[PDB]
């Protein structure tokens, strides 16, 4: 889960 959050943090 936390799909959007992970992607934004990964960069």
Image (cartoon, helix red, strand yellow):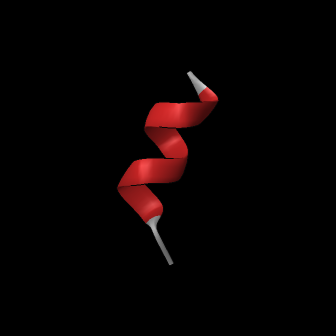
Q: Residue at x 44, y 34 (%)?
A: 8
Rendered location of residue 3, percent (x, y)? 45, 62
Residue drawn at (37%, 53%) of the image: 4
Q: Estimate the x, y position of residue 7 in percent, counting from the top left.
A: 50, 42
Q: Is residue 8 above or below residue 4?
A: above
Tell me where residue 1 appears, x and y as whole percent: 51, 78
Location of the C terminus (image quadrant): top right
Task: List the single residue furthest toward the bottom.
Answer: 1
Residue reaching furthest left? Answer: 4
Dividing the picture into quadrants, the one containing residue 2 is: bottom left
Residue at the limit of the structure toward the top, as seen here: 11
Is 8 on the left or on the right of 11, as rendered?
left
Q: Quadrant of residue 10?
A: top right
Say left or right for 4 vs 10: left
In the rendered view, does 10 fall on the left or right side of 6?
Answer: right
* Numbered label tally: 0
Above or below, 3 relative to 7: below
Q: Residue furthest right?
A: 10
**Residue depicted at x 42% and y 51%:** 5
């Amino acid at each position: 889960k936390h799909k959007i959050l992970h992607r934004l943090l990964q960069d």
